[PDB]
Length: 87
Length: 19
Image (tube, rainbow over the protein chains, first blue to last red):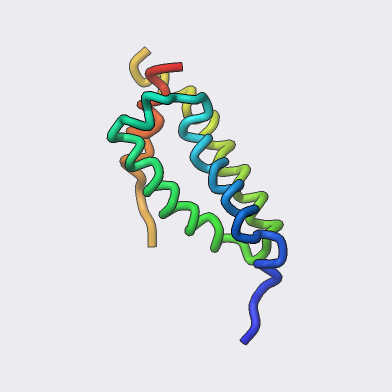
C-alpha cells in the first residue's frame, strides 16, 4: 500500500555509492593484493548482509545517511585498536 | 536477528597488519 519516503533519494546507483563507504571502513586504503586474498571474499558478502541491515534501520534516506556515518566512524577508529592487538 | 560479530574482528585485523 504505502511506505516511508524512502526510495525518494536512495536510488539504485546512488545507493551503490553508499555501500562502498561501508567497505571502505574495514579497508580505507587501497590493496590490489587484497582482491586476491580469500579474506576479501567475506568482506563483500559481509557488507552485503550488514548493508541490508543498515539500510532498513532507516525509515528515510536521511536517517540512512546518518547511521552510515556511525558505522563507518566506529569501525574507522576501531581499526586503530586492532593494530595494537599485536603491537 | 543479529548477535556478536567474529569475522568483523578478523576483517579489520587484515588491514591492521598492513598500511
